[PDB]
Each structure stands twice: as structure tokens, then as C-alpha cells.
Amino acid sequence: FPRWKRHISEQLRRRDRLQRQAFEEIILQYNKLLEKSDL
Amino acid sequence: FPRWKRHISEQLRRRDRLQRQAFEEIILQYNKLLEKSDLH
Amino acid sequence: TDDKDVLRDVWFGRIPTCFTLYQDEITEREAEPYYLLLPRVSYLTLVTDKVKKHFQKVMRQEDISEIWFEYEGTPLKWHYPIGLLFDLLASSSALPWNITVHFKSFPEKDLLHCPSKDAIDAHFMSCMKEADALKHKSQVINEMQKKDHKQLWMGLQNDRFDQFWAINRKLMEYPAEENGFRYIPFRIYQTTTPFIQKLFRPVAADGQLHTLGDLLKEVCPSAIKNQVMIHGIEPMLETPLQWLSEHLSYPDNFLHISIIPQP
Amino acid sequence: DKDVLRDVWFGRIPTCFTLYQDEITEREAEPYYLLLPRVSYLTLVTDKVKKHFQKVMRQEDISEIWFEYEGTPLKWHYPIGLLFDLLASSSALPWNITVHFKSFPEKDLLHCPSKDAIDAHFMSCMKEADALKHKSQVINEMQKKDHKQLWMGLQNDRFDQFWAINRKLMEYPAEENGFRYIPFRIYQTTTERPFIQKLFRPVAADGQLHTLGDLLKEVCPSAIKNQVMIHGIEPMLETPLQWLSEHLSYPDNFLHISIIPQP
């Protein structure tokens, strides 16, 4: 499609990788342990 | 400090922001919680 | 609903966040930090109900005070969307976003109160109504039934993409003969949390589509080594503004655009 | 320059050790999160991992431990940093390593020896490195007590303790104006492919110093589309080789250089 639309939608995937994909898994396990730690 | 040396020193700090500083604190906190479960 | 793939990746944008309770705060027990993924498009006061409760247990039954958030000495103004706050305040720093949680010493003259979820609902509608006033002389937001307005809210609050854009697609539509919105809803933020907002039309007398660069040249002429950030990305200046207001706006239909330096 | 040595030494790699799914467990098994030293070896940093998973398996279930990334086993004698740069740079942090206790590939992967014997591979690598730099002159004049201090300095993450001995290994006679040969090893797409290690001198015929480009032109002209990666950074190809051998080596005095394509 045009130059810019491809370029914009690339960084959105790049951003989610850098910011969400990295911490999604660890933060999920952290919270699960946190709840389990409330006895 | 010449071009290559400056540029090398910047990446090393850039690398530490991205790889170490991002995960050190949360990984630390994760492990403290884990000992509490091992010892239920 | 044009390029839904771009819309969904914007809507579901997340930001890894670390919530730590302030040290001077009286606690009955040590309180571990709360880690969380915050939605970039929602509001800080709307999505932190789980965080608030986490620190309620550690603190005494008194205070029992309104919760506020601080990022390195600066109180966080909840009227700004979470994404805009992060992009503008903390993006150049290292993840996760480190937010301090307070309960005492509310900065009465620096930060507005947020008393009910209804009050968030209020701010959200004021922003949309202001947005539509620019795009269609208030024509579309007024012609929708009130059951459509409370659906837009329930869509944002409960993070349901389809439910939201069930109503929002109309607001992104325009009369075919005009080929664009009357005016584009945008706000440009400098380093501090006084923004800039003038009037700007998406199409000239030439008929050509205006880009992000055209906008800045006429509204914020101090960019171009500055970087221009929207939802965490730096779109090409060549990006047509009408397309941005359609696809890169926040649920309040505004283009919250942050201007930050590099590094 | 002493600041570079410290950030090379203390480099880390966030890693997630997930137990291979095939394995049977008495109770549920958590992933072990951890920061691995780029300069160390998988051999040293994994009793904490072995111990973490020790709990959830009966003796019958447990066998010799080994590590996989994306189907390919991980060599015990490649530095952790180099393994990551070559095999996992493009992937998302944290580094996802699979832990096994069954189906050791005797055909494709060397056994994990006693910790004693990684120490053997380390010291032989230093010995080979010193042979190139000094005609083996310096490490043959050290007390045995120094070899175990180099090793235990790497093992215990004590920087100044290690570089107490290693500084002598980085010195040269004044008249020579640099090492005789530079100890280096180049790695291409995978670990299984043989690395390159030839003879190459840091000072030219003229007296001018040779750069990284000269090494690559002479030894691997396929890196000139491709990325040249040392300790996670891409130094300018105008970087003097002698300086790199001095400052960007791993503790085994070698320049483990990776050649990897973009992005």
C-alpha cells in the first residue's frame, strides 16, 4: 500500500514487541505469584 | 574522545538500558516472591 | 472501520508499568510493588482499581484518602490518556514505567481530583463533544441517542473494541462532498503537561490532502532535532492528517501528539 | 577506557528458563527468571536452575541437564553473551531457553563436564590467546595461584579481582606498539558451522594501526547487508583492532565476533 501506511503499521508491531511482548509473560507470572502469596 | 570510542561507549549504555535495566528490578522482585511459595 | 488492522493495534497498545508505594506513607505491613500492563488509550484513574486495592490492605483503615500518582516528583494529570503521559514523560527512560503511588499530601493546586468513575465518564464525553464540534459542527454527537453515548463509555471502560467502534465509526465518517472533516481535533504537548490547539482544516483550496508536516508548519513551527510521537510511533511527516484523525486518534477522537527530543 | 571494561564485564542478559513440556512433574513447574553474564558460560550459572526444577521431579524423572534454544542445543563452551548475539538477538526479551532432563543429544552436543573442566576450556583458550599475543611468554610466568584467580574472578563476578591478573595479559613491549597477533574468532549464521580463526596483526607495514574492516576484508569479505556484532553492539568498522582486542574481549582474551544479517 502507500509508503507511509506500511511504515506506520510496522512500528506499531515493533512498538508492541519492544513494550508489550517482552513484559507480558513475566508480569503475568509475577501477578500470579503475588495472589498466591496472600495466605 | 574520537568517533568510534564515543559511539562504542554509547551503545554499551544503550544496551544496558534495553537489556539489563529493564529486567533487573522485576526479575529481582519475582524471585523474592518465589521463595515464599517454595516455603508455602 | 477502514484499516481495522491499524485500529486494533492502537486500541490494544500496552505499557509495562511499575507501581511503588511512597516510602513516607504509613503502612501496617511491607507492600510489594504492583506490576501491570496499562492500556495506552484509557485513563489512569479508570484502570488502576486493582492497584489501589493492593495498597489498601497494607495501609491503616484511616487514610482512607484519595489515591494519586507521581512520576519523579511530578503529579500525573489523569485528564491526559495513559499513552500520552508515558510518551510525553517517560518514553526515553527505561521500561518499565516507574510510577509512585501516594495517599497522603494531595497536591491540591497542582492536580485535579477524580472522585467517581462517573467523573471520568464526564471528562471523556466533554472531549468527544469538543472533538465532534470541530469535525461536524456538533452534528453527529448530538444526533446520536443517549444510549449510544453510554455505550461508547462502557466500551472504553470494559475494553471492548467492537462495542466501541460500533458507535465510533459514524464519528469518523464525513459528508462525501467535503472529502474530509470540517476541522481536525488535535492537541500538541510541549515538555510540560500548556498544550497547543488552534484551528486547522484537512483539505485546502488546492484539493490536496494536508499532512502532519503541513499542520506543524502552521501550528508548531519549532519542530524541524525534535521527534514527533503519536501512540509511541513517529509517523512519516508525509502522513495525511485526515487519515491520522481517523486512525491514530484516541477514543476521545483527539490527536494527542507529543513533541520530545532525541535521545 | 576503564569504564568500557566494566560495562563489558557486567553485561547481562535477561533469561527465562522454561522446563521442556515433555517432562513429567509432581507439582506445577514455574519458569526461572535470571540475568546471565554475557562473559560467563552456561556451565557456571545453572545450578540455581537445576536446583529450582530439582523440586518438582522424582529421581527417576531427573537426568543430565542440558539447554535448548529453538530446537538447537546450546554449547557449554561458548560464552553466554556470544550465544545470545548469534542465535537470539532478533527475538523478544527475555531470552527463552528450554531446560531438558531427558533425550540428551550425544551426537550433537558435548557433555557438561565437572565445573572443573569448563575451567579447563577457559584456561586453554587463554593459553591459546596468549600464544598469539606474546609467543606464550606471559601466562608461563604466572604462579599457578594466578590461573585459579583468573578463573574464580570470572566465576564470582569480581571484576577488579580478575583484572588484577588479566591486565598483565593485555600489556606489550614498548617497541612492538601492539600485540603480535590478535586472538579472535568469527561466527556466521549458526553455532554448528565452524568459526574462523586465522593469523592477523594489529599494526600495518607502515606503522599505522589496522581496523575492524581490515580484519574482515582479509578474513571474511562476506560481512561487507550483514551486521558485525561484538558484545551486543556494532562498533564502527573504523575501530582500531588493537584497541578492540584490549577492551572488547571476553575474559578468555578472545574477540568473539558475530556476523549476523538484518534486522
Image: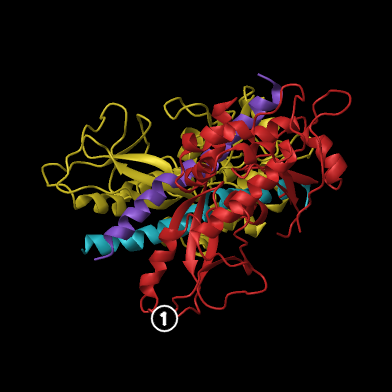
Chain colours: A purple, B cyan, C red, D yellow
Q: Secondary structure at mark 1?
A: loop
- Location of residue C119 by image quarter: bottom right
Q: Is residue D19 left or right of residue C35?
A: left
Residue bearing mark 1: C62
Nearest the eye: D26 or C80:
C80
Q: Is residue D118 left or right of residue D229?
A: left
Residue D204 position, x and y percent, is 74, 35
Q: Is residue D201 left or right of residue D115?
A: right
Nearest the eye: D221 or B4:
B4
Q: Is residue D157 left or right of residue C204?
A: left
Q: What residue is shown at x 74% (from left), y 28% (from top)?
A: C180
- The amino acid sitting under disc 1 is Glu
Nearest the eye: C162 or C119:
C119
Residue B12 position, x and y percent, is 62, 50
- Location of residue C171 by image quarter: top right
Q: What residue is shown at x 76% (from left), y 21% (from top)?
A: C177
